[PDB]
Image (cartoon, coloured by chain):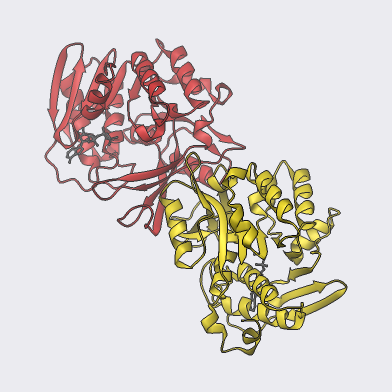
Chain colours: A yellow, B red
Amino acid sequence: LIASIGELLIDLISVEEGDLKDVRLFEKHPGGAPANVAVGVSRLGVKSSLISKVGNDPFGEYLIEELSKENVDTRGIVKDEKKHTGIVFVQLKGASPSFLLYDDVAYFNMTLNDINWDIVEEAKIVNFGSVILARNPSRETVMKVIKKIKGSSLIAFDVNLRLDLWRGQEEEMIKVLEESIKLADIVKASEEEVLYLENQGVEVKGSMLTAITLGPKGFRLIKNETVVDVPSYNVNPLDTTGAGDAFMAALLVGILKLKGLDLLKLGKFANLVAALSTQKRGAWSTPRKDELLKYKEAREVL
Amino acid sequence: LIASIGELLIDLISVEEGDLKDVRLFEKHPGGAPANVAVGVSRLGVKSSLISKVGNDPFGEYLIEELSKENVDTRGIVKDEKKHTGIVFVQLKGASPSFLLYDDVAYFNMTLNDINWDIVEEAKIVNFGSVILARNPSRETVMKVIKKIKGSSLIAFDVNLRLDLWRGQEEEMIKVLEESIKLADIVKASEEEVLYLENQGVEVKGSMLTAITLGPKGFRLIKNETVVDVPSYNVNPLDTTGAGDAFMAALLVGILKLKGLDLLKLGKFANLVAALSTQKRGAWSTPRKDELLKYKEAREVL
Ligand SMILES: Nc1ncnc2c1ncn2[C@@H]1O[C@H](COP(=O)(O)OP(=O)(O)OP(=O)(O)O)[C@@H](O)[C@H]1O
Ligand SMILES: Nc1ncnc2c1ncn2[C@@H]1O[C@H](COP(=O)(O)OP(=O)(O)OP(=O)(O)O)[C@@H](O)[C@H]1O
């Protein structure tokens, strides 16, 4: 029903605060925006699959197992015999969070052969990554997939901009992103990204819907000429790490379930799911359907 | 006086038992045989340098700093503007130790332009690993360097066989190892490595001295046809992880200090350093000079 295609990797999360240079301990967890959204969609009660590529190693097996536990279809996840599973060391704490991502990994080495078309086509909504586009052959491969299915399925794109991933090739970045946006019916981006990109002559807009996140403050929806600000519900945030992908998961589930872009319904659903997710720890903080039924906002969609 | 050239990387050590797939926590430490030996040499009171390459990232800075605290000369460690610092996830525990090494990293990307010849000009002994030979351009860069210095500095080679690093290129492995051995005045290898290579038709012996390790049973020193068996000191091992590199550091310092090749003195000094290193944890377990003066076998050499 809903399929995601993009980076699937291991997050080595710093246990203590400090620069990556000084951090002594790391805790491993499954990561990758597309995979995080795929799990969120699954927890919302919607069948979901992930098309990605991991290495034929212990980390690869771990990721497939963890996704399997969340009920995400992994049949579309290929194992690479040359490249090892993706990894990124992260420091989520402090005033200036940082990361060290290793790019010669399996998810950046996808080829058309690696794509399971039966799955990408059965889906009503196809969500693809921005990070996955920083390196070929995955870039070419993904752009080819999105262009091919366009029109047959709704396309969703989260800008999720990472400048460090395009150093020395920013021009190409502008092209790839602009091209991606133009293919997406549903586009998600933080206000910062929106600003940074328009300042490059790039319009951050989805042909069907645009969702601009405004941090803990809230989000904003744009339908044609209609602009709606949605303040965030009150919560005593435990961890907002997964808020972005939880928000995206809810947004794609809401669109799927609600015939007619009722931004009021949709807006309330995403706000609810995103806010509540700040109660869970980690990259997969999307609340389960069984927990959202108590709310009228969710009952509408779910 | 003593220079090491080879791999320098971050060891992500599993804090708990289990397959890497299930390990949750990893503790980061400096690793790499040549780096480990350089530290051991420095601790024994001899000035040592390391020629290697790390990425221009937090982990690269970490490694350079840790080596500097050990007084190892780091001028010969270059920063790669593209490739990231080497990393290896390791499970040292259990009966079946395992690891996951990422190969497209800085130390495997060394070119002749990365070689600080001055540091190489000073060295009376140059130590290099076989792991660094696993990939080009570093393999050719290292082979060329050692070939040029041959006859000006004593050459030391620790076979340190890691078959997983040569899958698909085992024939080449046999050729490079043999070339490296024939280029070395000093060769170190485990009995297991000696048998594997002899069976491959390769003779494991240095032109000046050969040290065959028998693990906890001690080692064997060989010059020409004069053999000297050195049984292990009687100790209760706490951690043998760094014993090999501690042994190599002692062997080189001994050769540098002791007038002739008195195998008895050399054997006693190396044995003492190795045994005591088993009392310290981690890859850098070589005892410091200050902790050795109270030993007769050490006073001579030191
Ligand atoms: N403390 C909070 N209380 C209520 N809702 C929140 C809170 N934090 C985040 N949210 C909701 O989740 C959405 C996610 O916001 P966040 O600041 O994580 O941006 P994002 O879209 O994840 O950006 P990025 O791509 O940089 O991670 C917000 O727009 C907001 O509505
Ligand atoms: N239990 C022990 N008691 C005393 N000495 C030991 C013990 N274990 C190792 N050693 C000393 O340290 C030296 C290092 O040998 P070790 O068995 O660690 O192999 P190695 O040369 O390090 O190879 P590898 O890379 O496979 O570890 C030995 O030759 C020995 O003298």
Residue A117 visible? The answer is yes
User: Viewed as shown, does residue A62 lie left or right of B186?
Assistant: right
Q: Quadrant of the C terminus of chain A?
A: bottom right
Tell which quarter ligand 2 is in: top left
User: Viewed as shown, does residue B89 lie left or right of B215?
Assistant: right
Up-down: is A265 above or below A255? below
Q: Residue at x 36, y 21 (%)?
A: B174
Q: Residue at x 62, y 66 (%)?
A: A2
**Residue A209 occupies quadrant:** bottom right
Q: Residue at x 65, y 56 (%)?
A: A129
User: Viewed as shown, does residue B58 lie left or right of B262?
Assistant: right
Front residue (pair A29, B10): A29
Q: Quadrant of the N terminus of chain A?
A: bottom right
Residue B259: x and y in percent read 25, 16
Residue B177: x and y in percent read 36, 21
Up-down: is A37 above or below B179? below
Up-down: is A35 above or below A291? above
Front residue (pair B87, A302): A302
Front residue (pair B80, A4): A4
Number of marks present in the image shown: 0
Looking at this view, name the residue that lies furthest to the right.
Answer: A225
Residue A276: x and y in percent read 58, 80
Front residue (pair B229, A2): A2
Up-down: is B106 above or below B184? below
Residue A27 visible? The answer is no
Residue A104: x and y in percent read 56, 42
